Length: 143
Length: 143
Length: 147
Ligand SMILES: [Cl-]
Ligand code: NA
Image 1 (cartoon, chains in turn yellow, brown, blue):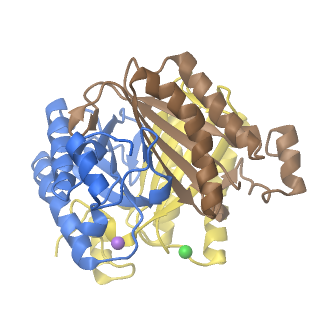
Image 2 (cartoon, helix red, strand yellow):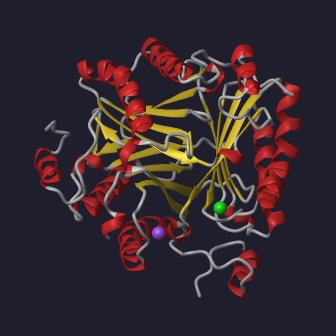
């Protein structure tokens, strides 16, 4: 896997504790770290939707999580990669949400590779020597 | 019409009442239910932007609604389908906002159908008998 | 330039508490606006919305990061890719983002995501073609004008 993952997680009040949010973000992060990404690429942001602000099927829902996942274009081109990705994220989303009766939905949207920068730097190529330096330092390194 | 609609609606303070948000969400939901979707697919989330956090033309705007509509890719390929969709949403957005003096903007962004799941399930093919079960039960039926 | 400054644009800027002051948010929004205005866009097309993320709601490499800005830039889909024009777009936005964030020790990330022009409307009107006479009317009036 290469490129940015940015997750936005909107949810009802009294649905995820601060500890569950941290746990979820860290399982998301682990998944990408396992694909070889520098961990600091992974951003997960939660937004609690006050009651009155969220509608599913036209009605307020008190127990939902809506995830939007932003990737870069052509980062998971094969059916095998895409299927593997869904397996890997279901492995931590399902066991968190199902015991809570949570209804959840995710989808992945893809963005052009060449318009992404971190601290004003275009990140290095997957597998490159420069990426190993970024991983080691866990920060954007200027060369 | 394939796939999920997820709407994000950002707006200024003192611009939409809780009653107007609920009514808007019901109208959006009715639009997609009329296309044949299960009601529960339709998500609409509002975020009020405090004064000092929203800028249009570089100035704070006290009376705006900014909409982001997330659809699946390849769901409206013909000009006729696309034009019909825009007519159908303008039919409720314009009469709500115009008399209030609101400035509103929407656009539609697209995501691949194969990376979309609800409650850990890939939803049924559009127009399928399996989809009809999801419409009828208004929930993600495991099968 | 060109292909990359046609619109919409919509900027979403998520950030930690006590990271950007209200004055800085306003100054950034004006800088972003001027960048697109310089390429002939009507000023009112440029929307910039900030969302403060409370402590405990933001994770970067698993860290609850207290000093970050995460930007999402929504643009119109392009007919083609141009490295020359793209580099011009990135140079112009880095010219204001970097000087604001770097002296504050902020870690920041942006990317651009694209949307089809034909499903975009402002006040219920499809905006005029990039570079057209109709667009010049919208520039002058700084609002959507029916034809
Ligand atoms: Cl692909
Ligand atoms: Na490009």
